[PDB]
Amino acid sequence: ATRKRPR
Amino acid sequence: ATRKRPRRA
Amino acid sequence: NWSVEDIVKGINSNNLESQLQATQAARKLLSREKQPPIDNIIRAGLIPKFVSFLGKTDCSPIQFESAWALTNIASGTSEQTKAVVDGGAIPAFISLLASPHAHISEQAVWALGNIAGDGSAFRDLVIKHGAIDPLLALLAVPDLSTLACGYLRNLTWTLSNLCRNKNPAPPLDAVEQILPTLVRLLHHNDPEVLADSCWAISYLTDGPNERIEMVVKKGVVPQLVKLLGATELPIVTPALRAIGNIVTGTDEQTQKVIDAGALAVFPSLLTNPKTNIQKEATWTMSNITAGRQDQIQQVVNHGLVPFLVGVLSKADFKTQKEAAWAITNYTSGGTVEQIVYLVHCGIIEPLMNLLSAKDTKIIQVILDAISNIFQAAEKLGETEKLSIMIEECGGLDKIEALQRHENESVYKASLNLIEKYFS
Picture 1: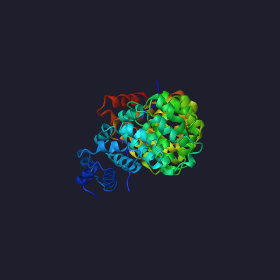
Picture 2 (picture 1 turned 120 degrees about the vertical axis):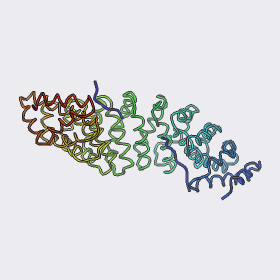
Picture 3 (picture 1 turned 30 degrees about the horizontal axis):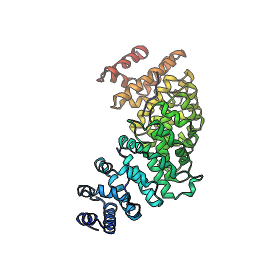
Picture 4 (picture 1 turned 180 degrees about the vertical axis):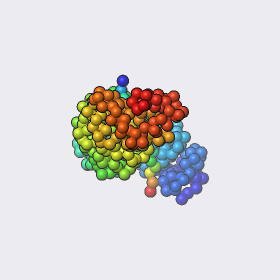
């Protein structure tokens, strides 16, 4: 459940 | 989208 | 210069010196004109001849001239690069890496860099032909400072192209073989070597967390952070891209960036005159505020929340959108006290002003943030006071305005927030 957003 | 260089002079 | 017809007549002479002079005339045509007649040279059928000249060990001049001519053909369109590959150039250039003449070996390095720079297929084909071992052997000296500057720059750039592109990423064992040499180059003080080494690291970190791990475990993060503070924009740009890539990974990988001191550079990154630096830095911040609440606390302690308020207040819209994400992530993971601190820094007014943006996704990001702040307010017994702030910012009635908005998606919280808080 990550809120990291890829490039 | 490539990455290239000519050699000039 | 010569016409292509004369070059063809000289190359067809079977007289080695006539062929050398014609090949030199081709290289001058290919290196001097802007709009060199590359297609005319290819259509005349000269590439197989140039490739055969690469193998003439008894005439090092014609090896150099044909290597230079083929380098510049390979620097063209993908079709022009494919013509060089189709003529057998790859294994001929790899053999030339062993030339006793440094000017010839560096020209073969350059040509292989142009071929690899075409894309992942030719990159991987250069690797399959065995380029990596002889390329790295050219760098096997105790001190890189003994190598010629231009030679070292060309090797670094070609190695960075072998680290290039994403679909697929380069073979794992090729990356492992190259990385120690790449880390040496990242510590070499020449601005162009540093820039291209940083680009290579940014490529290698763009991908899954396992790719990030193999870079991070070589210990390069403190050096990336040092380069993140360089004065040369061509160094800062790829260093910042690599740092940003690393913080898309795990919480531990993100913590290495913080531990290395990266946050101390962000006051200047988030105000940087170059729009692309601000955007990239604000995107990196949004992936750090998506971390653990002790990582959010580091953002707070470094004084970066006022800088996020600033970017949200005034910036290129794309940068403002990344700042809205940073805020929503922060509100999503932060403690009640961290959210209180964010409001005390003035986040509400610039956040309400961007609800007038015609981009739909930023409206949903901002309304998620407003929602997250209200639940913090609920936990304190404190909700109504927030509601008061919002409407004096004009934010109230531009929330109702958004219940007309086309999306079922903006419709949700627009009514939710009002039924639950305002009216």
